[PDB]
Amino acid sequence: STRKAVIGYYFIPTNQINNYTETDTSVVPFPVSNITPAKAKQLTHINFSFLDINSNLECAWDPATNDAKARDVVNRLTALKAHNPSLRIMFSIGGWYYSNDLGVSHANYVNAVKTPAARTKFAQSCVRIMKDYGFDGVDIDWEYPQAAEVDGFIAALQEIRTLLNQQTIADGRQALPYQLTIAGAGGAFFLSRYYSKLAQIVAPLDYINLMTYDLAGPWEKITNHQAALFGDAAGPTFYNALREANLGWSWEELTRAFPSPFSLTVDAAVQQHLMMEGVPSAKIVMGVPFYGRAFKGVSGGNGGQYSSHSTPGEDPYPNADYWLVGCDECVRDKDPRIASYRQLEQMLQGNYGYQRLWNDKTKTPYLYHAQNGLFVTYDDAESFKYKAKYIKQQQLGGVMFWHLGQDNRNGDLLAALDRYFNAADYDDSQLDMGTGLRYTGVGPGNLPIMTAPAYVPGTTYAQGALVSYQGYVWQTKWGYITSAPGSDSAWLKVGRLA
Ligand SMILES: C#CCO[C@@H]1[C@@H](C)[C@H](OC(=O)NCCCCCCCNC(=N)NC(=O)NC)[C@@H](C)C(=O)O[C@H](CC)[C@@](C)(O)[C@@H]2OC(C)(C)O[C@H]([C@@H]2C)[C@H](C)C[C@@]1(C)O
């Protein structure tokens, strides 16, 4: 019973920093003061976002940033630590806008990690920004290094870790050591870019915060849940790209690890991490969305699930038709495709025509607007019970979420996560996790415990025979085999001894 991490992004754009105020929500909708002492206590980390990498290949604020206002906002966050001596204010470098393959700063990420000298300079800039502004650690949210750049990225994290460790010693911060995290891919297509080197990536980290949300969106042909915990056989499935990663595994090893097609769920991403040797469950943090994704143009029959739709994917949103009925924040932000949980409660409570439905396979809620043909996929305090139960059962490190401003005013989502993990009186021992589709892949990092008769030399084993030998349970790939398990290619390591 180590405390689960509870990691909340605090995102504030440059224009809001530069006009920062705590008394006008039309300029800053979500000021630091909305994070009350009670919320501060429920959080373990706050990820201040986003810093960038500049063309000097250093960690830097957006250069339009007013530095005194920036320091002041950051000081308000670090003052929160007075209510909670476990609390850290991290900062994040990257995000989609800055760091995506076509993002505005993308070449800076590539070049910052490309060579030994560039990495030294970058790493030093991170620690220096951390100490100058009073942050408690470094989060990297590069979406995403491509297979060629992965060795540099790894080396960059290793170097940052060493510098963080020096800093923790210099400041005598062993009670709350400076930390290093990344925001990891939560679906196999991006994950496949660095999957083969996952143990190396995770080794220098305190946590890898899986972005296990945005698993559906307007870029797909068919509506779906953006953060299904388990799979729905009625729903779409996807090619498992991990089976083409450069792993050096055999056909049978790849097949047993990477079923395809597969359901793109939270459970899949988590298992895909656990399958790798050297990736410990305690370092894996499950991301959850504090917002819904909305689609229009959907047909009926199944609550708007798994339907074609007409939601534009362009960015910025390409006209002024704000068709997400009742969503006032969408008008403010000029995009009807995303609604905060905060806004969604209001849409459901007003006379706007939505029903709240529940998929008992995915263990996630959804809104359906029968009259206009709208579907919204989001998470709430109910879906979080199952996700928290899963976090406990799988011995994950905790939960991360984007983002704090999207909680409702009383902070019920955060409170709920804090309760499912820490409340003495909350009991989920009978919470039924459903018959949704589990990801069944097995790999070297997550072998099940098994028993079988001991291997006997001289015996002819038929295809599919199971024996135990030198700590493991092995299975013949064909028959008849007589070789000692592990000595040639005929035997598959399927389990570990009892
Ligand atoms: C101008 C523009 C946007 O362009 C998109 C296109 C670029 C899409 O852009 C958008 O959806 N924009 C909104 C993005 C939300 C941010 C959150 C992401 C997660 N990050 C986080 N949530 N991070 C986080 O929480 N961090 C803590 C993008 C998601 C996408 O799928 O791009 C794919 C790459 C796999 C392309 C580039 O190949 C894309 O694929 C498809 C879907 C077939 O579309 C075409 C092109 C070819 C098309 C030409 C480009 C668009 C229209 O699809």
Image (cartoon, grey):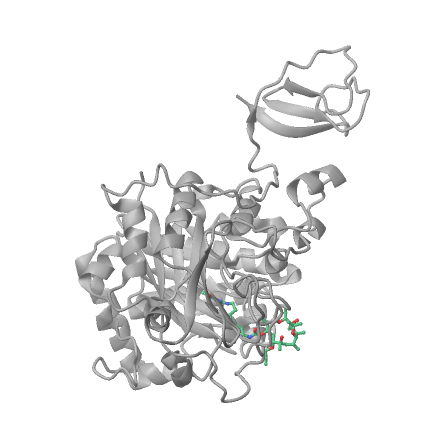
The number of callouts visible is 0
Q: Position of residue 101 (x, y in %)?
A: 60, 72
Quadrant assignment, res 223: bottom right
> What residue is shown at x 55% (from left), y 43% (from top)?
438
Q: 412 or 322: nearer the eye?
A: 322
Q: Quadrant of ligand 1?
A: bottom right
Q: Residue 343 appears at what percent x and percent y? A: 35, 73
Q: Is residue 102 visible?
A: yes
**Position of residue 73 measured from the top left corner of the image (x, y, whole percent):** 27, 75
Q: Nearer the viewer, residue 320 or 350?
A: 350
386 in relation to 92, above or below: above
From the viewer's side, name the closer residue of 50 and 417.
417
Q: Is residue 61 left or right of residue 233?
A: left
- Horizontal side, residue 329 vs residue 300: left or right: left
Judge by depth and name the residue closer to the eye, 420 or 447. Answer: 420
**Residue 63 appears in the figure:** no
The percent position of residue 302, horizontal first and vertical second, equals 55, 61
Toward the right, the furthest residue is 480
> On screen, 352 above or below 396?
below
- Residue under the image location 62 percent in, 69 percent down: 308
Q: Image quadrant of residue 480?
A: top right
- Vertical comparison of 196 with 253: above or below: below
Residue that protrudes farthest toward the bottom in the picture: 320
Quarter the N terminus occupies: top left
Q: Is residue 111 above or below residue 165?
A: below
Which residue is found at the position 61% from the left and 38% from the top? 442
